[PDB]
Image (tube, rainbow, N blue to C red):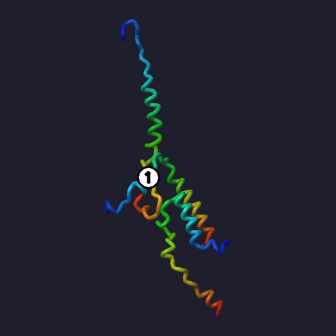
Amino acid sequence: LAPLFGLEQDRYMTAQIFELMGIKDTHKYLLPLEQYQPPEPSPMEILQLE
Amino acid sequence: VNPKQLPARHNLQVVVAISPNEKAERAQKLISLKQLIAADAQ
Amino acid sequence: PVTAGSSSWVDRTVWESVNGTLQDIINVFCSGDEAVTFVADNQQDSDAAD
């Protein structure tokens, strides 16, 4: 079921849990998915592919 | 702080009778959540 | 004191119950360092709760 349980579903689950316990989730490191740019790959996998 | 910028009571629930130690309680919850978010990399 | 020889020693009972209720009342509301704390239902209005 992981292929369907992507990132946004996990984020919504964690956000619901927080709302149940701690409301303001944006106050800190966790970022709204709308402005989450993808990670920048590192040179390690690049040189390994090379 | 603009007064017009604030919401209305329709979307503001209120709570009373808060224990002093509740802060610490929250802290515990937080660190618990921390562990959780540490286990999931997505 | 209807009469001197009666020595009508009063029984302070209302005061007793008043205090017995007031102590619990203050232990309910004024026990915490804070009075109340607003809580919202969405993240779009959580910045105003605190």
Which residue is farthest right? A1
Note whether B28 is above or below B39 in the view shown: above
Apparent side of residue C8 relative to residue B37 in the rendered image (left or right):
left
Quarter of the image containing the C terminus of chain A?
A: bottom right
C41 or C33: nearer the viewer = C41
Assign a secondary structure to mark 1. Answer: loop
Q: Position of residue C6 (x, y in %)?
A: 40, 8
Query: Residue at (54%, 64%) from the top-left corner?
Result: A15
Note whether C24 is above or below B34 in the view shown: above
Q: Chain of mark 1?
A: C
Which amino acid does the dot numbered 1 rest on? Thr
B25 or B13: nearer the viewer = B13
C30 or A8: nearer the viewer = A8
Query: Residue at (44%, 31%) from the top-left corner?
Result: C19
Q: Position of residue C5 (x, y in %)?
A: 39, 6
- How many numbered callouts? 1
C35 or A14: nearer the viewer = A14
Quarter of the rendering containing residue C26: top left
Category of crowding for the residue at label 1, using alpha-carbon neighbours closer than 10 angstroms: few (below 14), some (14–19), many (at least 20): few
Which residue is farthest bottom? A50
Which residue in the structure is indicated by mark 1? Answer: C37
Q: Position of residue B39 (x, y in %)?
A: 63, 68
Query: Residue at (59%, 60%) from the top-left corner?
Result: B32
Q: Position of residue A1 (x, y in %)?
A: 68, 71
Which residue is farthest top? C5
Query: Residue at (61%, 64%) from the top-left corner?
Result: B36
